[PDB]
Length: 21
Length: 21
Length: 30
Length: 30
Image (cartoon, rainbow over all chains, first blue to last red; front, top):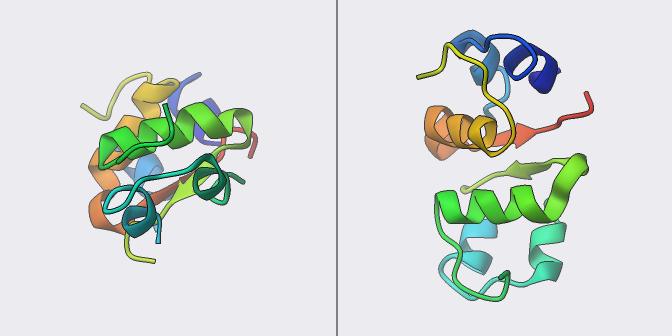
């Protein structure tokens, strides 16, 4: 999930864009 | 939509909570 | 703090504060 | 600005900046 991938671990642009509509 | 209801017009708690999961 | 004009990052912050753990969806074209 | 630890309102702000017009969904329990 977004918190585990981007807060608990270092985020990435790939990860973030998976949550755009 | 959220922008028309809460930015272009005055928001409300009812409106905002319609967009919680 | 919710009964005002909330635009842009201000709107997103309000959703964050109000929705808490549930999270939310922000769609400015629908 | 995206390749770091992004928590809380910081994460939501990044999604806002990156996703732009498309908007996004923020789900911290999935």
